[PDB]
Image 1 (tube, rainbow, N blue to C red):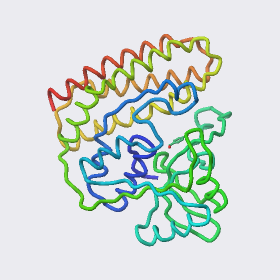
Image 2: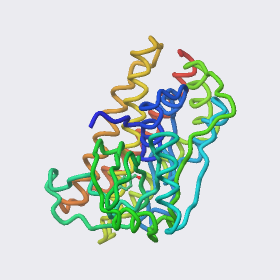
Image 3: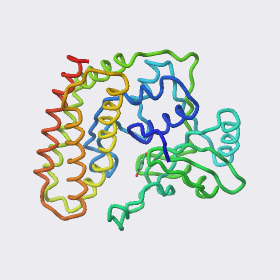
Image 4: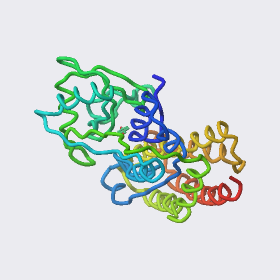
Length: 307
Ligand SMILES: *C(=O)c1ccc(O)cc1
C-alpha cells in the first residue's frame, strides 16, 4: 500500500489517519521528530529497547501534538461485549478507528523474503487502522508495514484482548481530538526537537546502547540483535523524514545527513547478520554505534547553527 510511514507503529497509525482525513499539523509534527531512547531493563526482557521512542504509545509525540497543535490523542479502553458496537459508532462518525492489536495475529511482514524461515511468533502490541466492520470479519490497515488485510471477527477480538510482552491490551483505541487546532512553522518544530535532543543528551543513549552491545560477546541468546535491527528502523525513518523535509521546505542542513542515514543502515545490516550468521563481531557493531553517537551529537549542534 501507499501508507504514511511515520517513524514507528504509533506515528504511522496517527499519520495515516491524518493523511486520509486531511487533519492539519499532525503529519509535519511526526515528520520533524528527532529522538532516541535506550532502556537496559527492556534489553534484558526481550522488549523493544531502543530506537526513536519507547512504546507502544509514543508519549513524547503525544506531548509534541498537544504543545504544538493543541491535538490530544485520547486513549479509550473498552470490553469484549462493547468494543465492536463502539467501533461501528466511530466508523460512522470518523470513518477510521485506531486500535491497539497483538501483532501475533497480524501477518504484516514476510521474514521468508530475507531468508528468515524460523521467526518466532511473539505477543507484541502494534497498531492497526480499522476501516470496515462486517458480520464475521473486519478490514484493517497496518500503515507501518504498508499492508492491509481482512481479519476474522474471532481473531480481531482475540488480538484486542491479549496479554503481550509490553502489557495487557483491553480493546484500547486512540482518538485524535482538538478543541481548536494550533499552527506551527517547520523551523520551530525542528529547533525544539534538536535543542531537546541535546538538552536530554539523547546521543548519550546511543553510547549506552553501544556499551551494552560490547557486553553480549558470550550471550548465546542473540534475539537482542534481531530486536535491535527492528527497533532501529525508526531511526532510519527519522533520518529519511528529515531529508524529505529539507527538500520540501528548502532548509539549510549539515552536509552529512545522508552519510548518517547510511551509518544507521550499516548498523542494522550488521545486527541482522550477527543474529543469523553466527559471527563474533559484537566489538565491531559496538564501535559503529559509539561512533554514530558522536556524529549524531555534532549533527544536532550543526542543525541548530545552520537551520
Ligand atoms: C509496531 O507496533 C510493531 C510491533 C511489532 C512488530 O513486530 C513490528 C511493528
